Image (cartoon, rainbow, N blue to C red):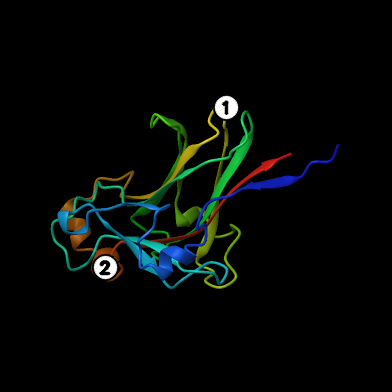
Amino acid sequence: PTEVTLPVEVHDAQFVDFRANSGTSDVWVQHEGSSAGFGDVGSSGDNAFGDGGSARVRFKKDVFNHDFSALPGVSQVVEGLPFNTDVTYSLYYCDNKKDDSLSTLYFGARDINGNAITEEYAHVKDLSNAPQGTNKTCFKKVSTTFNTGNNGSVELFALMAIDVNGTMTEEEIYASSQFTSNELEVRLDEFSLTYKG
């Protein structure tokens, strides 16, 4: 035999339609509630490899009822994964807020009952040498590998956690340039699922 790398299709994986439709999507589920304080999800023209846009996740700098423990971002129920297979879930993650970034990417897969199959965290401080986009090089590849077991269909998520390992206060976050200037934002593009066959 010879090993090959095979895809499982993620729909609108480059946010082409998401961008064209200004955040509206029947495949991407936004985790958001901007004016209620649970973060904002929308499209950005920035992208990793020149296609579509990206999902921009932020807490708006002109909104002052944020719950910075909220986990805004996107999810998608993806079908057609092979059973009993180590699948690599990747996306490209653009955080421009440097090693001090208050954002951590929280990404993974859940099963049909909402149970975590895999959970992974990624912070830009650890991504300086990761594979990158050819267009916006801030997009860095992040990956998590998990066995599908009996889960041919999974919910992929990619959410943003603020100050996930610290105890900054709400006031300290509001006073930070990462909020007042950058809206604590990150951008997501270029989702993939691969496995070896």
Residue occupying image coordinates x 29% and y 64%: 178
Q: Amino acid at mark 1?
A: Gly
Vertical relation: 165 (above or below) 84: below
The residue to which callout 2 is attached is: 177
Under mark 2, the amino acid is Ser
Residue 66 lies in quadrant: bottom left
Residue under pointer 1: 149
Relative to 14, is 165 on the left or the right? left
Q: Nearer the viewer, residue 40 or 8?
A: 8
Between 135 and 180, the residue placed more toward the observer is 135
Eyeballing the image, is 135 above or below 15?
A: below
| Left or right: 155, with 196 as reference point | left
Q: Find residue 43 and report its horizontal and vertical position in percent.
A: 38, 66
Instruction: Label 1, secondary structure: give it.
Output: loop
Residue at 61% from the left image edge and 59% from the top image edge: 131
**Which quadrant: the C terminus?**
top right
Kindly report the distance in space between the C-alpha atoms of the residues bearing marks 2 and 1: 44 Å
Asked if residue 28 is positioned above or below residue 178 in the image, the reply reads: above
Q: Position of residue 92 (x, y in %)?
A: 52, 58
x, y percent for residue 132? 58, 63
In primary-sequence order, the first of circles 2 and 1 is 1
Image quadrant containing the N terminus: top right
Q: Which mark is residue 85?
A: none
